[PDB]
């Protein structure tokens, strides 16, 4: 499972894999990997299934409550910290969570917080979480450029995922792409790896500079 | 029934303050006097001892003068019983502050805990308030000398000379007049001893019918050295002023 | 016992405890807040005829809740301290959990809930103090002034007065300040506040204490000396009709 | 209106609070129940009043079991009776689990008894106001006990209560005196029916439904049973015989 | 059940009075004559222990209790009130000084504890004070010999010599003259006997009088019949025979 | 006098009724009238829904509590709510734990204890509500009358709410006819609408806001509302 | 004074009745339910020319399709409003769907009885019940648009119109004639204000009224002040042309 | 660990805190302030787990800031330290200890002297001119005792710290990518945005 999210001029690019397995045989090419808390917050699945599921709907209750009662737009800054503080209470209770708390509010701009079961909350432009993460990081890093267009940003994201898909076998059923904007998230379709592999291997010429 | 055997008197009067609290104030004004004088090279405390006789032990005059700290002491006006409960809690509060922040309690900080409990006593339970007023004598290294007072109403103020217990009006009137800010310990004592005389009507006033303490800079400290006088030391100073009364 | 009938309605619909609470306020000191539109001025009376005390051992009229949130009161001293302690715990808890320097309104919601709380439910008796909570919310040039009561209500208010001589200061705010068009100068806002509390204190500038709060933590309390120069000026305006 | 009628957080000048006295008075204007001790058992009977044809015969029952071999009927205030029994059950079960035996009647009596006494030493907890005729057989014989409002209980050999008490007690003592204690359990059923029928003569502006039960060592084989079928028809026959019919 | 009397049952008035206390102070006066002398050469306590029926024994009645091996107490007032407060007084003396600090309590600090209980049962609603006044006499190297009274008020004071119960004013007076700074324990036993003689006659014999002393003691009962670690406790209470014998030489 | 046996739950009378019981009995009458009748195979409740404001909309006031149980109220609605709340909880706990389906008598007894604990403290209270509970178990059909006074009798017929006595007198007469008629619904339902119309004497009868509720051997718990009461007027 | 177990002859505590009197002394709130919308109007009330608008609460959101109007004391309704938000939030967590108008109402009113040191599986600990009634409106998929009147006495009635206030007399009688099964959302707002100006003794303006409605078009929408004034100005023409 | 150094010059406390987190081959994050400002003349720097750090930090800042307003003055470095240690000593007994070991670099602004404190995750308190965490000190105590002796201006402290960091990156196998330097004095907290020989 390999998930990445990077901050750029147009908002946020969030790109994720999907894969469910019975053996090494791909049982379903399908499963969520963005838990859509509400349209303004995303939390991405890379932790325990139940842990992520339980606390992230519960996080949806604290956001909904804050805005209903206090009549104030809740920050990403507030969303991560509510989460981190409860996490430390359920620490050494058997918790496994690796999520990135994504939002793009009026008052902060695009903001991506990495939040783990250790309770750590870090702000960064670039966070990759997984276990094909080091390889996925490579593709992204060598072609990184903050000033970029949303379309070209999507193609770089999806090639990065592919790179990680090919080597690591815990990704690569399908890719789901989402671009997270101010007014909410826009889905950029579901792309099959079979068709996507042959184009990239020829096209990119990274690790493929003499075709292999 | 017994839901109507409730006194219902720890609720407000229309006078802007609880029944029991206002009535309790009267009780104070019918028990011993404490006088607090804050000087420019000490703090002088005088209290007139309520019952003095041979049947009592006359060599004891710590019956209302307790030091809460190394540099904070209080004077009681009210009844022994009422006092003791706040004394013990102020002592601990001193130790909690000391332990947490590595520094001694400031005089107002200490005052403020005691006063929030006094209010509390009527605010939770319905129980009766205290019957004690303190005049606090202390030093802090942020304002110089501080001399304060609290009452069972939970209102507190700072003053440069005040009296509480019986004969507040008479003593306060005289104090405001002779007050200076170039007085020394010894000039204050003389002053104190005059005031006490003018509020007590006697042939003579004796040294064992007084409880006295002053908190001066000292000459064994750059701090403040707390001197608790006992009858025989009261006898000496009475000669020194040449004020026999 | 004491968990019941401290507070109940009459058939006339008055509450006993609330009705005797409002009476402690009229008796006590005087506090007023006048808002500019880029300042908020809080003027306070502290009234003592007995002169044998200092200001530096008598508690201040304006207490800091935060550097950019201030609290003023009229009423019992004892009760007000209880309320002040909650507001500081609520400032720091908010900062911790939502990771935003405080919004002044939320803090009103906490102090007001407590005040509601001891009235509605027994095992505690109500408060006898009314408060003014004022400050600036971050990223605002617009002043905030609130009033909260022992009832536990609150609302936001352009100038407001409580305590002794509420009528007089009220008339003055009605005829000399507008909700529509207030002072736009800091100076004129100071002038107005002094004018209002001077008519009622029945002393000079040595028993009016002015504190001016300009945006986000900028607080300066003008001294007796500074107020006197406006006090002079005021006797001159009044001798155009005398 | 003395606090000896609004509270039981004191002792009275009459050694009992007025409200407990009043419980005793309300048992007597009530419904009739008896209890007949015999040399091998006990028999219970109660008068169930008929006020309408809207009531169903024996689908409302007043004699309720505790355990399986102790039968309880009571006269007086209905709610208080439910609560007493519910308690009676919790004791009985606790005893069976804990000691691995059905509970003795002097034991069972001390357990209910202490609980009736408890509700009579608090100023806001309602007294009981039922008199309970109860009993059964255990491993050293049959026992008939009667429990009162006030927490008073003794063993009985014959017991009577209610509206028709006077009449009931008259017939009942005659028969008990005549007999070694009550003769056979079987004979006692008929006799029991006569008393209840005889007591009904004291209230003919209502009808009755005769209800009997028994608990007998060798004539129920240790169990408490309702008295029905033939055995109920026979007791009726005997009753209508003597009281003319 | 609880929660019906949660208002205090002392309240103030503009005369400042606390109802319960004034009534309870009266009770102390109506007790039997008990006295305390500090002779500044020990401490001597005496009281009357007296029948209340012809077939009541008095050798099953004591008014002298040990609070700890070396602090003793005497009282006037209500019998029950004294036993129950004494249990609680015992409790704190034993658990909080002999385990925590490993030694017997200092008197004055024990005076603070006993006061605090009495003042507490007045401050808390639903209950009353104790209707007794105790005289707590003890000895320590650090403080010398000491004597305090603790009132029903929960106020305290020290008293060179005092008396409470019936014939209070006269008993204290006669005593004050006969009290010297430097006074011999035998003479101080006579003065006590003499006083109690003035309160009662026609039932005054020495075997109905119970006298206890702080000073002389018996090591042989403190498990130091053999070689001592130390001398140990200074309170030792007389038997009747010792009392009667001295009464003859009164 | 008044103040001796009013609010005071700990007191008694030589008669055993306090003021708080007599007011409670009056409170039942100030709710709307509801009548009960049963055979031995069915139990029926006929209840009038009459609004208490001009604009008010009709809502159910017969509440199904379980598959084999329900109640209708007459008296105070908050008081009615708490009891219904405890009874639904009680119904569940018996079914999970003992698989036990309640008979009316058993619930009743439970109900008496609950009121009883609240009449042993000043901070609780007695109620102000009567209830007619119907249920069909394996001992046939049942109708129970629950009273705040703790008097529980299981009856063939009754009425509670205002003007009880119209219906009681009719119900005691048609008694003999109705109890021997088994396996036939329609006659017992029709007879209930006639009974309740003798309770009324000056108050309307509504031909689409009557609500009849039935339980039985061949009937699981159905409330007929609106249209479906027509053919029994 | 008065016990928490001391009834009137009718079964009803002193304290319960007494709350209900204070309700009627509050401000006027009027709600009309059709099957095209529920319109809620209240008088907001300006207590002085220096009291700021929309700092006093009279139109509150329980949820994004659910509103309430209050009458009585404003702080006393706050404990209710809190409980109502909490009930709404929780039901949505558990069941991922909307609370019904009825359900929501019941949950608040169970905890508005209480009072005294009693308990029976219900925790009661208040000194008084609340001094406030609220008209709770919502729309739910099943029953559509509904209006419910909550009494703080633990009593609840289903309604198609109700008015409360000190202006209750005029407004309920007017409401009966005005009521119909459906009529347009714009006609309804205009008509509400008409009824309000009648029971109001003074000139009706937007600095003492706030309007609100509930739509299936876009959920709970407070109909704001600027937009409301322009309707009051039309009101002056239509009303002085029937005269 | 997280390499955390300190040096106390005659007027100031200079504290050096790693600027990177390195995950195999590449630096995953490389913008890392591993220190949190308590107050304008109280700073505390940290090493331990990543999560303990921020959770303790925020809890502690909030408490101190509450004390600052209630008592109406800025709490001493001495007041903070005794507070910090006492909380850490309790946590060890409990299921979850806060496992952050700290350096508190302060200006005592009331008597005008800089103070540096090393307080361990257990509660082991020391005042030091210079100190270090872990295996760092084997190599860098050998350069600091030898080449430095007290009463040396601030710039000399910068050059020494860089020499210490270079030797660490060379010879010890841990990898932490230099230091980001912060100076605590009466003028507050300033960033040294150079680390090139400073």
Image: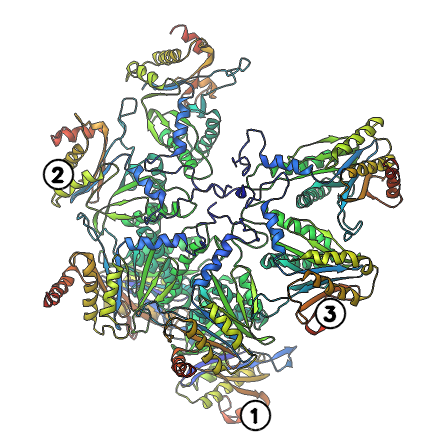
Task: Bin the neighbour count of mark 2 within 10 Å (Cα to Cα): few under 14, some 14-19, many 20 and up.
Answer: few
Q: Position of residue C202 (x, y in %)?
A: 18, 56
Q: How is the image coloured?
A: rainbow
The reply to whether dot 3 and dot 2 touch (C-beta < 8 Å) is: no
The reply to whether dot 1 and dot 2 touch (C-beta < 8 Å) is: no
Secondary structure beneath label 2: helix
Residue B124 horizontal side relative to residue A195, left or right: left
Same chain check for tags 1 and 3: no
Residue C235 horizontal side relative to residue B135, left or right: left
Task: Bin the neighbour count of mark 3 within 10 Å (Cα to Cα): few under 14, some 14-19, many 20 and up.
Answer: some
Q: Residue furthest top?
A: E248
Secondary structure beneath label 1: helix
Dividing the picture into quadrants, the one containing residue F170 is: bottom right
For label 2, the residue is B187
Q: Which mark is residue H163?
A: none
Quarter holding the C terminus of chain G is bottom left
For label 1, the residue is A198
Can residue B243 be spotted in the picture? Answer: yes
For label 3, the residue is F233
């Amino acid at each position: 499972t390999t998930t990445l999210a990077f901050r750029f001029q147009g908002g946020i690019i969030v790109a994720v894999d999907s894969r469910a397995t019975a053996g090494n045989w791909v049982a379903s090419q399908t499963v969520k990997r963005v838990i859509e808390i509400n349209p303004f917050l995303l939390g991405t699945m890379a932790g325990g299934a139940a842990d992520c599921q339980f606390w992230e709907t519960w996080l949806g209750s604290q956001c909904r409550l804050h805005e209903l009662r206090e009549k104030e737009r809740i920050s990403v800054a507030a969303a991560s910290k509510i989460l981190s503080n409860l996490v430390y209470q359920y620490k050494g209770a058997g918790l496994s969570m690796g999520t990135m708390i994504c939002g793009y509010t009026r008052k902060e701009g695009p903001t991506i917080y990495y939040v783990d079961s250790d309770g750590t909350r870090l702000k960064g432009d670039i966070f990759c979480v997984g276990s094909g993460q080091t390889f996925a990081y490579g593709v992204l890093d060598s072609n990184y450029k903050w000033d970029l267009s949303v379309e070209d940003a999507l193609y770089l994201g999806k090639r990065s995922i592919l790179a990680a898909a090919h080597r690591d076998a815990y990704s690569g059923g399908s890719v789901n792409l989402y671009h997270v904007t101010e007014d909410g998230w826009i889905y950029h379709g579901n792309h099959d790896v079979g068709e996507l592999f042959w184009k990239v291997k020829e096209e990119e010429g990274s690790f493929n500079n003499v075709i292999g | 029934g017994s839901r109507r055997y409730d006194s219902r008197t720890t609720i407000f009067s229309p006078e802007g303050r609880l029944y029991q609290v206002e009535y309790a104030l009267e009780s104070i004004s019918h028990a011993g006097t404490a006088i607090g004088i804050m000087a420019s090279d000490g703090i002088v405390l005088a209290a007139e001892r309520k019952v003095t006789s041979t049947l009592l032990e006359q060599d004891t005059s710590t019956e209302k003068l307790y030091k809460l700290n190394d540099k904070i002491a209080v004077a009681v006006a009210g009844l022994t019983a009422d006092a003791e409960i706040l004394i013990n809690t102020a002592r601990i509060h001193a130790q909690n502050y000391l332990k947490t922040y590595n520094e001694d309690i400031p005089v107002e900080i200490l005052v403020r805990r005691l006063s929030d409990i006094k209010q509390g006593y009527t605010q939770h339970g319905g129980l009766r308030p205290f019957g004690v007023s303190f005049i606090y004598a202390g030093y802090d290294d942020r304002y110089g000398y501080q001399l304060y007072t609290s009452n069972p109403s939970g209102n507190y103020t700072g003053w440069k000379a005040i009296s509480v217990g019986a004969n507040t009006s008479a003593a306060q009137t005289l104090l405001q007049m002779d007050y200076k800010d170039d007085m020394k310990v010894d000039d204050a004592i003389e002053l104190a001893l005059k005031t006490l005389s003018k509020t007590t009507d006697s042939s003579a006033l004796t040294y064992d019918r007084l409880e006295f303490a002053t908190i001066r800079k000292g000459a064994n400290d750059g701090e403040v050295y707390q001197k608790i006088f006992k009858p025989q030391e009261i006898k000496d100073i009475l000669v020194k002023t040449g004020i026999t009364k | 016992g004491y968990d019941r009938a401290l507070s109940i309605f009459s058939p006339d619909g008055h509450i006993f405890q609330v009705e005797y609470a409002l009476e402690a306020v009229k008796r006590g000191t005087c506090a007023v807040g006048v808002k500019g539109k880029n300042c908020v001025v809080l003027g306070c009376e502290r009234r003592s005829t007995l002169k044998l005390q200092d200001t530096r051992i008598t508690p201040s009229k304006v207490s800091k809740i935060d550097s950019h949130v201030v609290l003023s009161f009229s009423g019992l001293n004892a009760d007000s301290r209880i309320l002040i302690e909650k507001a500081r715990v609520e400032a720091q808890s908010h900062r911790l959990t939502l990771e935003d320097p405080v919004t002044v309104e939320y803090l009103t919601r906490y102090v007001a809930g407590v005040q509601q709380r001891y009235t509605q439910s027994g095992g505690v008796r109500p408060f006898g103090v009314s408060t003014l909570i004022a400050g600036f919310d971050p990223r605002d040039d617009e002043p905030k002034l609130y009033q909260t009561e022992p009832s536990g209500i609150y609302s936001s208010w352009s100038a407001q007065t409580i305590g002794r001589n509420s009528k007089t200061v009220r008339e003055f705010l009605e005829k000399n300040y507008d909700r529509k068009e207030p002072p736009a100068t800091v100076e004129e806002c100071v002038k107005l506040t002094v004018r209002s509390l001077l008519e009622v204190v029945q002393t000079g500038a040595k028993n009016i204490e002015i504190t001016v709060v300009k945006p986000d933590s900028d607080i300066v309390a003008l001294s007796s000396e500074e107020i006197n120069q406006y006090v002079t000026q005021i006797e001159q305006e009044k001798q155009e009709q005398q | 209106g003395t606090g000896y009628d609004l509270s039981n957080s004191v002792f009275s000048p009459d050694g009992r609070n007025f409200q407990v006295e009043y419980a005793v008075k309300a048992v007597e204007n009530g419904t009739t129940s008896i209890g007949i001790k015999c040399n091998d058992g006990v028999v219970f009977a109660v008068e169930k009043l008929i006020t309408s044809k809207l009531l169903v015969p024996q689908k409302n029952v007043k004699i309720q079991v505790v355990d399986r071999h102790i039968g309880c009927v009571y006269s007086g205030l209905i709610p208080d009776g439910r609560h007493l029994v519910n308690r009676g059950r919790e004791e009985a079960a606790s005893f069976k689990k804990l000691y691995k035996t059905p509970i003795p009647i002097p034991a069972f009596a001390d357990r209910l008894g202490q609980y009736v006494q408890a509700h009579t030493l608090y100023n806001s907890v309602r007294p009981f106001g039922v008199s309970t005729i109860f009993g059964g057989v255990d491993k050293n014989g049959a026992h008939l006990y009667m429990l009162e409002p006030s927490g008073s209980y003794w063993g009985y050999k014959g017991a009577a209560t209610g509206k028709g008490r006077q009449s009931a007690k008259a017939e009942l003592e005659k028969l008990v005196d005549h007999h070694p204690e009550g003769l056979s359990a079987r004979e006692a059923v008929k006799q029991a029916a006569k008393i209840i029928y005889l007591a009904h003569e004291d209230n003919k502006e209502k009808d009755f439904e005769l209800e009997i039960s028994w608990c007998s060592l060798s004539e129920t084989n240790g169990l408490h049973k309702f008295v029905k079928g033939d055995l109920l028809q026979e007791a009726i026959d005997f009753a209508q015989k003597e009281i003319n019919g | 059940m609880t929660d019906r009397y949660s208002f205090s049952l002392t309240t103030f008035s503009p005369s400042g009075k606390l109802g319960q206390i004034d009534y309870a102070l009266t009770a102390v006066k109506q007790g039997v004559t008990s006295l305390g002398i500090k002779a500044t050469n020990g401490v001597v306590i005496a009281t009357e222990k007296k029948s209340s029926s012809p077939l009541a024994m008095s050798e099953t009645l004591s008014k002298v209790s040990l609070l700890t091996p070396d602090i003793g107490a005497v009282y006037s007032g209500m019998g029950p009130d004294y036993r129950v407060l004494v249990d609680k007084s015992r409790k704190v003396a034993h658990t909080s000084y002999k385990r925590i600090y490993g030694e017997y309590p200092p008197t004055k600090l024990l005076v603070s504890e006993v006061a605090k209980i009495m003042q507490e049962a007045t401050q808390s609603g639903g209950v009353r004070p104790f209707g007794v006044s105790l005289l707590i006499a003890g000895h320590d190297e650090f403080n010398g010999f000491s004597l305090y009274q603790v009132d029903p008020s929960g106020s305290y004071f020290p008293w060179k010599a005092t008396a409470i119960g019936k014939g209070s004013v006269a008993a204290k007076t006669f005593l004050e003259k006969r009290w010297n700074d430097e006074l011999e324990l035998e003479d101080a036993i006579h003065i006590a006997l003499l006083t109690l003689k003035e309160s009662v006659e026609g039932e005054f014999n020495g075997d109905t009088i119970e006298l206890a002393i702080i000073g002389d003691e018996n090591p042989d009962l403190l498990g130091y019949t053999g070689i001592p670690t130390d001398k140990g406790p200074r309170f030792r209470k007389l038997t009747s025979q010792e009392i009667n014998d001295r009464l003859e030489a009164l | 006098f008044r103040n001796n046996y009013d609010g005071d739950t700990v007191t008694f009378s030589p008669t055993g009724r306090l003021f708080q019981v007599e007011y409670a009995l009056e409170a039942i009458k100030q709710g709307s009238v509801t009548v009960g009748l049963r055979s031995n195979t069915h139990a029926v409740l006929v209840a009038l829904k009459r609004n208490a404001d001009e604009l008010s909309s009709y809502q159910k006031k017969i509440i199904k509590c379980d598959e084999h149980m329900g109640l209708s109220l007459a008296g105070l609605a908050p008081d009615a709510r708490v009891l219904s709340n405890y009874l639904r909880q009680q119904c569940n706990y018996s079914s999970l734990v003992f698989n036990r389906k309640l008979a009316v008598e058993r619930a009743g007894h439970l109900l008496c204890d609950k009121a009883q604990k609240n009449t042993q403290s000043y901070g609780g209270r007695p109620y102000g509500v009567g209830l007619l509970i119907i249920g069909y178990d394996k001992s046939g059909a049942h109708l129970l009358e629950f009273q705040p006074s703790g008097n529980v009798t299981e009856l063939y017929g009754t009425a509670i709410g205002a003007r009880s006595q119209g219906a009681k007198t009719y119900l005691e007469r048609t008694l003999d006819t109705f109890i021997k008629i088994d396996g036939n619904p329609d006659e017992l339902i029709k007879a209930g609408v006639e009974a309740i119309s003798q309770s009324l004497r000056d108050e309307s009868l509504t031909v689409d806001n009557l609500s009849i509720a039935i339980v039985g051997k061949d009937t699981p718990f159905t409330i007929y509302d609106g249209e479906a009461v027509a053919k029994y007027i | 004074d008065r016990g928490v177990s001391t009834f009137s002859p009718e079964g009803r505590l002193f304290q319960v009745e007494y709350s209900l009197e204070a309700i009627k002394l509050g401000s006027t709130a009027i709600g009309i339910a059709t099957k095209e919308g529920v319109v809620l109007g209240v008088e907001k009330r300006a207590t002085s020319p220096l009291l700021e608008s929309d700092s006093i609460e009279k139109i509150v959101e329980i949820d994004r399709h659910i509103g309430c109007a209050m009458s009585g004391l404003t702080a006393d309704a706050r404990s209710m409003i809190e409980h109502a938000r909490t009930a709404a939030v929780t039901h949505n967590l558990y069941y991922d769907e909307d609370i019904n108008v009825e359900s929501l109402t019941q949950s608040v009113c169970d905890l508005a009885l209480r009072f005294g040191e009693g308990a029976s599986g219900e925790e009661r600990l208040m000194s008084r019940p609340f001094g406030v009634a609220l008209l709770i409106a919502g729309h739910d998929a099943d029953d559509g648009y509904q209006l419910f009147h909550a009494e703080p006495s633990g009593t609840f009635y289903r309604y198609n119109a109700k008015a409360i206030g000190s202006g209750s007399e005029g407004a309920q009688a007017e409401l009966l004639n005005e009521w119909h099964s459906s009529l347009t959302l714009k006609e309804a707002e205009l008509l509400v204000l008409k009824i309000l100006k009648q029971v109001m003794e003074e000139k009706l303006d937007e600095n003492n009224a706030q309007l609100s409605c509930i739509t299936k078009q876009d959920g709970f929408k407070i109909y704001d002040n600027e937009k409301t004034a322009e309707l009051i100005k039309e009101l002056k023409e239509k009303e002085a042309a029937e005269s | 660990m997280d390499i955390i150094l300190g040096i106390r010059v005659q007027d100031s406390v200079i504290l050096a805190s790693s600027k990177a987190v390195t995950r195999g081959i590449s630096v995953l994050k490389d913008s890392d302030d591993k220190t949190r400002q308590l107050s304008p003349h109280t700073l505390m720097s940290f090493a331990g787990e990543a999560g303990d750090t921020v959770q303790f930090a925020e809890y502690i800042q909030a408490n101190i800031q509450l004390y600052s307003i209630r008592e109406d003055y800025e709490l001493s470095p001495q007041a903070v330290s005794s507070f910090v240690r006492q909380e850490l000593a309790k946590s060890i007994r409990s299921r979850r200890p806060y496992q952050v070991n700290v350096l508190i670099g302060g200006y005592d602004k009331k008597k005008n002297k800089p103070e540096l404190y090393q307080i361990d995750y257990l509660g082991t308190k020391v005042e030091l001119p210079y100190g270090a965490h872990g295996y760092s000190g084997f190599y860098t105590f050998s350069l600091l005792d030898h080449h430095y002796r007290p009463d040396m201006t601030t710039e000399e402290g910068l050059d020494l710290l860089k020499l210490c960091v270079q030797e660490l990156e060379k010879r010890m196998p841990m990898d932490f990518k230099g230091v980001i330097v912060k100076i605590v004095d009466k003028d507050g907290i300033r960033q040294v945005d150079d680390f090139q020989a400073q």
